[PDB]
């Protein structure tokens, strides 16, 4: 597949996460903004990479479905988020943000959505602290990156980079499945904070489930 660029940030078509040797391809890459008044104001550039073994797993169900057929099924996005494979996500800052300020928003969409469904156990609470701790001493000038590694077993790994480059040596590893998927679920889920990314991951992945 081809490279996807999001507002200058250049997400290459393949990438090996920090601490991994397998190859991941780029599922999709879109912008995240919020609605200041009435304007779409861009803050981050997100890319979602999926392990190569993922094409087989998803194709079991989604082969031959159009880009819009895939783009409209919340299952295609739940499958990806919770797929029994590895997922690598890079968040690149278009606007300046601080780790303390990034992690807060992510956890309040989670530790809230878990209280909406009664799944905010001492697990989530502990995972979100270790989460909110890895981000606290960091500030992300535009160009820096946040790199999450989602494992098949639900093990989140939080690396950082000064630029769009994925570092060689890994980061922290929060050993909780919900918080792992919550992070990804919050980017390309039903309430995904990046529908552009969903659009890219729907278009690209549809052209691979026909080959
Ligand atoms: O205007 C914003 C930006 C937003 C924000 C910070 C970081 C990030 O990554 C994405 C959004 O913080 C907010 C919180 C709010 O309740 C309402 C508006 C905003
Ligand atoms: O690149 C994008 C994402 C795109 C988008 C928004 C919402 C949605 O549901 C699907 C796509 O909207 C935008 C609006 C803008 O002014 C600038 C960039 C974009």
Image (spheres, rainbow, N blue to C red):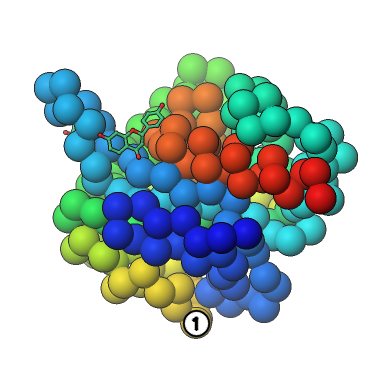
- Please tell me in which quarter of the rendered image ligand 1 is found: top left
**Relative to 207, 162 lies left or right:** left
Q: Position of residue 65 (x, y in %)?
A: 75, 31
How many numbered marks appear? 1
> Is residue 188 rendered to the left or right of residue 138?
right
Up-down: is 125 above or below 176?
Answer: above
Assign the N terminus to one quadrant of the image: bottom right
Residue found at x 64% / y 55%:
50
- Neighbor class of circle 1 (other Cα within 10 Å; few <14, some 14-19, many 20+) is few
From the viewer's perspective, tell me whether residue 201 is left or right of residue 125: right
Front in this rendered view, residue 78 or 136 = 78
Q: Is residue 175 left or right of residue 207?
A: left
Nearer to the camera, 4 or 145 = 4
**Residue 188 spot, x, y in % from top left:** 52, 36
Please say whether residue 23 is visible from this viewpoint.
Answer: yes
Which residue in the structure is indicated by mark 1?
Answer: 168
């Amino acid at each position: 597949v081809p490279e996807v660029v999001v507002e200058g940030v250049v997400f290459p078509p393949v990438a090996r996460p920090p601490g991994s040797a397998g190859s991941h391809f780029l599922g999709g890459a879109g912008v995240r903004g919020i609605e200041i008044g009435g304007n779409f104001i861009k803050f981050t550039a997100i890319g979602v990479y999926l392990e190569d073994a993922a094409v087989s797993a998803l194709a079991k169900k989604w082969a031959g479905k159009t880009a819009d057929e895939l783009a409209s099924d919340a299952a295609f996005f739940r499958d990806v988020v919770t797929g029994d494979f590895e997922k690598f996500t890079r968040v690149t800052m278009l606007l300046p943000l601080t780790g303390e300020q990034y992690a807060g928003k992510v956890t309040e969409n989670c530790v809230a959505f878990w209280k909406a469904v009664g799944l905010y156990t001492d697990a989530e609470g502990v995972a979100v602290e270790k989460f909110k701790e890895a981000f606290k001493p960091e500030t992300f000038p535009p160009g820096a990156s946040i790199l999450f590694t989602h494992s098949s077993t639900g093990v989140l790994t939080v690396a950082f980079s000064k630029d769009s480059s994925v570092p060689a040596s890994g980061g922290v590893a929060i050993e909780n499945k919900h918080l792992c998927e919550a992070v990804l679920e919050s980017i390309i889920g039903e309430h995904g904070v990046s529908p552009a990314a969903k659009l890219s991951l729907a278009a690209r992945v549809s052209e691979l489930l026909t080959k």
